[PDB]
Amino acid sequence: TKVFKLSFKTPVHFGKKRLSDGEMTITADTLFSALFIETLQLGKDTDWLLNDLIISDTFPYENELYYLPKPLIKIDSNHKAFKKLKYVPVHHYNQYLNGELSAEDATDLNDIFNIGYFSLQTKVSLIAQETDSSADSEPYSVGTFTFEPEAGLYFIAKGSEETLDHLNNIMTALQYSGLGGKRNAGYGQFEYEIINNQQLSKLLNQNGKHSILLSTAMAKKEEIESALKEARYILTKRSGFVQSTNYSEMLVKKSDFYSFSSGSVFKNIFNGDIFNVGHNGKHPVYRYAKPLWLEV
RNA sequence: ACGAGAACACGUAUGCCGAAGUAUAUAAAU
């Protein structure tokens, strides 16, 4: 159960809906997809790395601070500053759950949150009839994000030791390919470091009555009734396309799927599952929904 | 099996065009 930390040195585009849209963090779905396809490019055995690996969503970090997303618990007071905040440092993570975080404290934390910036890159396309004959060029836009020199992303993983070694190898291999969006266009390379934060390790090693879903998950058919007993949650529509499956890419697109977001609180833990979103393809296409809980 | 995948912020044009380093004033009072 080691955690990986990522550095890019070149901006990467994530994106939610349109190429000009930009993001800082990705969900476990994309990471699982990318790691899987990288395994397939290496051509190793997927079953081991199919139903044994547990991954968190990606999370931003700064020079020396690690953060987690905001738990959607019901705090009874200001209800303005707390809305604007997304991420919490580990220093006061349990303090916020208790209620020690002050409104001015939230103000301060939010102030420190400068961990990158967003930008729009313009690109022009002359593959059209602009060069061939009488026509115009095709400008379009992309959205990219530039992390600070000591800023990047990290995930929290758990599984068997053999699973961890395989993940290590695959992560190395992927290091040089991309992630995010326009990988081949010059965005999203990375060098990674495995660091063990004692405090975060403790954070994973608590025990309590609540539990914070850190990944993008959704229980099976036969667990949902008992899972949804007392929860505070957000649904997050996940859509997207697929790579080297059927003849027409524009014809291929995994069906819109829904999962809980990454700040929900649950009473009854559920194991998740890797759901097939496949239809009319030459292979099954995997979307990831399996939780990693922080039990407090 | 990464809201993906393809896509040169490209192609046209330059520092021009007119202006005088000019205007008088003894190599001089023994």
Image: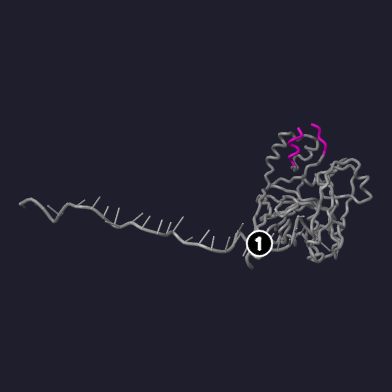
Can you identify the residue that label 1 sits on? A125
Label 1 sits on a secondary structure element that is: loop
Numbered range of the magenta stretch:
A73-85
Q: Nearer the viewer, residue A54 or B23?
A: B23
Q: Residue furthest right?
A: A222
Which residue is at a point 89% across and 40% down the rendered structure image?
A230
Q: Amino acid at mark 1?
A: Ser
Q: Chain of mark 1?
A: A
- Asked if residue A74 is positioned above or below residue A196 in the image, the reply reads above
Task: Answer with the quarter of the image where residue A9 lies.
Answer: bottom right
Instruction: Let me know if residue A83 is in the magenta part.
Output: yes
Q: Residue furthest front?
A: A134
Residue A250 visible in image? yes
Q: Quadrant of the C terminus of chain A?
A: top right
Q: Nearer the viewer, residue A257 or A131?
A: A131
- Asked if residue A25 is positioned above or below residue A183 in the image, the reply reads above
